[PDB]
Image: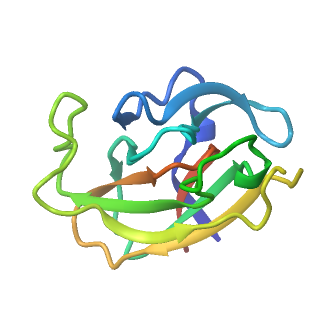
Amino acid sequence: DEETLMDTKWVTSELAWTSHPESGWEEVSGYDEAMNPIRTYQVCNVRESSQNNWLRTGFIWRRDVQRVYVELKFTVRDCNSIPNIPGSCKETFNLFYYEADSDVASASSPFWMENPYVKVDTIAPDESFSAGRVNTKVRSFGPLSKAGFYLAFQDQGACMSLISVRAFYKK
């Protein structure tokens, strides 16, 4: 038994998450594996140096949940399949969370807050398009003690697409 706290596939308009910088992660009209229309995020600045692209979700109320699970579905381009690629190309991204007692963040505020985004994990693909298949990975974090949290993603020079994100808890 499970309950969903947030799912990107619920959204029919726009996620309108916060990209820092704007030239990094980009929201796009996309498709899941079953060709449901859904909102996706992508980033692929593979020929530029010094990439540190962050993306932060909206605020998610945690209820009374101690440990949150996060299901990510994503695709990654094999670095070595990209013509004349610099050696800095990456194939992983990082997942973080940020606990808060209220929706303190703002897309107009500076991105970095008093407390750190706390790392959940470095996420690697099982398969990368080179052809490969959509990757599905589940990670968790906690114990939580504040009213809610944000999730956040860091790219540093990969070419990938975040197809969906679902935060849930196990009952």
Left or right: residue 22 compared with residue 11: left
Expressed as whole percent of the image width and height from the top left, the position of residue 110 reads 16, 38
In depth, the one of 137 and 22 nearer the eye is 22
Rendered residue at 49%/73% (across/down): 140
152 up-or-down from 115: above or below: above
Left or right: residue 124 compared with residue 60: right
Expressed as whole percent of the image width and height from the top left, the position of residue 42 reads 58, 37
Q: Quadrant of residue 2?
A: bottom right
In depth, the one of 7 and 15 nearer the eye is 15
Quarter in which the C terminus is drawn? bottom right
In depth, the one of 6 and 95 nearer the eye is 95
Expressed as whole percent of the image width and height from the top left, the position of residue 41 reads 57, 36
Can you name the residue that lies furthest to the right here?
Answer: 131
Q: Quadrant of residue 120?
A: bottom left
Rendered residue at 47%/61% (across/down): 94
Rendered residue at 38%/48% (across/down): 52
Rendered residue at 89%/50% (across/down): 131
